[PDB]
Image (cartoon, rainbow, N blue to C red):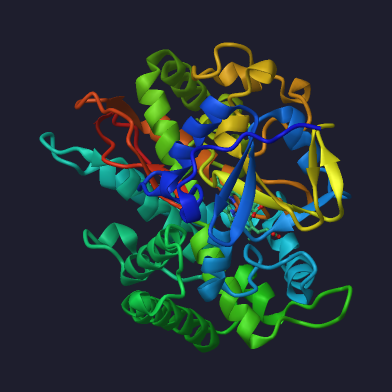
Length: 454
Ligand code: HEM
C-alpha cells in the first residue's frame, strides 16, 4: 500500500492550473514522464488517477472490476450528444439497445457493402491532388478531413457533404469544432456554472442548433428518397433490438446521427494525417509501403480483397496509432472497493484514466526504442502482451467503428502511395492540435503524380 504521486497543487485550485494550455494531453504526458506509471490529478470537485503502465492498465481493463466512466470531457459532450453510444453509461437502456441495433452494420462483413462508396470519396481526393498546379501544395489535415467527413456522410447516411467542392469550412464542422472547443475549455474553468460564462452557453446553444439543422436535412432527405439503402441510418430508423424487441426512439436516433457524424470522421482524419507525417519523415518505411501498394493495387480502383492484402499499410496505421492514438484517453470507474496493482486502494466509484499515448511508450513492453516509428513491431501482433495496445478502448465499450476506420484508412493510404511520390518541402516540425482528439496542424506536403490512371 503506497502513497500515490501527485503534481504541483495551487491551493484551492488543486492541480487545475497545470492544464491551462491548448495541449492538455501532451502536458499530462510530461507529468507522466516525471511521476511515472500513476498519478492523482485533482480539480475543484473531481479527482482522476492517470495510468501509464501496461501493468496497471491490464487491471483497469478487467470488466469485472471497472466499467466505462464518462470523463468530465464526455459529460460536457453529452450536452449535445446525449445518450448516443459514446456518451452513454453502460447501464443505460439506450446503450445496449443501440449497440445491438447497430453492431451488424459496422462488422467486417458490412465493410464489403461500404467499399464502393469509400472508393468514390477516395477517388475524389486522388483527383484533387492530381489537379494541383506545380507551384501548389497539399494541406494534409484539411484534405484528409474532407475525405473522412464525406466518407461517414455517404456511407452512413447517404448524404453528400461535398467537401471537395468547398474551400471554406462546412457550417456543420464550424459549429462542431466550436462545440468541442467549448467542452475542452470548460474543463479549465474552476466553476463552469458561474453566470460569468453565460455568453459561452448561449453560443454553444447556437452551435447545437446548427448541428441539429443538419440532422434535420439528413432525416428529411431520407424520408423523401425512400429506403433504397441499407446503411447506418436505415438500421437507426427501422432496426429493432433482439433483446427487447424495441427500436430506438426519435430523440435517441437524433443523438446517434450526431454521434456517428463526429466520431465517424474526426479520429480517422487524425490517424491518416499522422500516418502521412510518419511516412514522409521515414522515407524507407514509405518506400516499403509504396512497393506493397504498387504490387497489390493492380486495378484502376481497389477491390475489397485488395485492401485486405495491404498488410504493411495496416502495420503502418497501427504504428501511427501506437505513437499518437487519436482518441488519447479513456476513463473507468471502480465497480467496488478494491486495490490496484497491489499498491493503490480505491473506493467504489473512483475514476481512472488510461493515458493511451504514454501506455504505448511503456519500455518494459516495447523495448528502449519506443519513440521510433517501426511498423515491424506489428508483424506478429499475437505476441504483444494483453492490454498493451489500446487505441480503440476496452471490452464491450470498445470502438464500434474500428472496422470502418481501418478499412477506410488502409484503402485511402494505399491509393495515395500508389498514385503519388511525396515531398516534405517545408521540413515540417510536428505540431499536434488538441480538440479532445489529436491531429497534426500546419502539415503541408507536395506530391508528384506517378501518372497512373484511375
Ligand atoms: C482511428 C479511428 C478511431 C479511433 C482511434 C477510435 C477510438 C475510440 C475509442 C478509444 C473508443 C472508446 C471510448 C471510451 O472508452 O470512452 C471509441 C468508441 C467509439 N467509437 Fe471510435 N475510434 C475510431 C473510429 C471510429 C469510427 C470510424 C466510428 C464510427 C463509424 C467510431 C464510433 C465509435 C463509437 C460509436 C464508440 C462508442 C462505442 C460504445 O460505447 O458502444 N469510432 N472509439
